[PDB]
Image 1 (cartoon, rainbow, N blue to C red):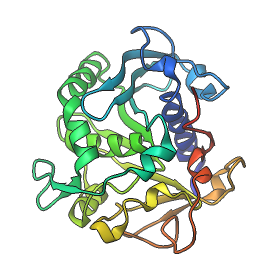
Image 2: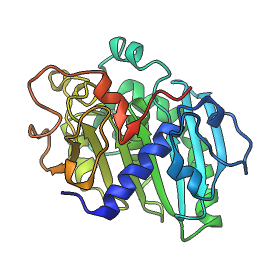
Image 3: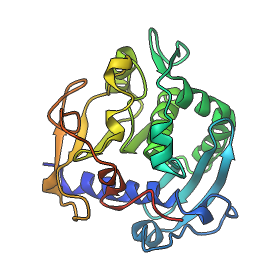
Image 4: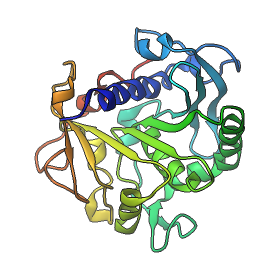
Length: 269
């Protein structure tokens, strides 16, 4: 169901997202190589993967993650980290929307995610553009797991349309805005958005649609189990805004399914 190349990208960006959790990658020297403890980003380590910018508890929403250089894969990767304590962030998630006409007409984003990105936007966009002018042939990829996935999605939306395409890869991302924004994320040029979900992960189910939310399309849904290796045949592509054949089904969700995207993610100390 997904080709081997796209699969290898899904696999690779999940490790870039996982790496963002390792505390050592949030305050590391520029030029230094990105490593992960617990054998959690071997593919990133195989590459010539060095830091460009490292950040922690920045702006309003404690924006943590890294901007990386990959000489091997030819990427400039902005990796947004999710919340340090996923369980807690979940149960205290606020569902408020606010208008983001700056990004698109009639669009409303989660107030929290949207404001957090805005906080660090000018700084992070400058760094990204420095890399783009230094490495004009590298492709810009924004990634993240959980709360980082929303950050990457909203950041991609805002920054596209400035001369360089930006692909987004999000792992277990919550819904990020209303219908109009979901339609925007579905058809925006200057990059593709690859929204990946896993079995019955709770996080893509929130905030609830009832609070005025929608998911962009399509959806890359991992059917393989928590703790089980994914193969290219376990990921089905589901098309349609707010589709119900993948993660958005009326069954009980689980927290553990959120921690298993290719390999463990969100757990690196």
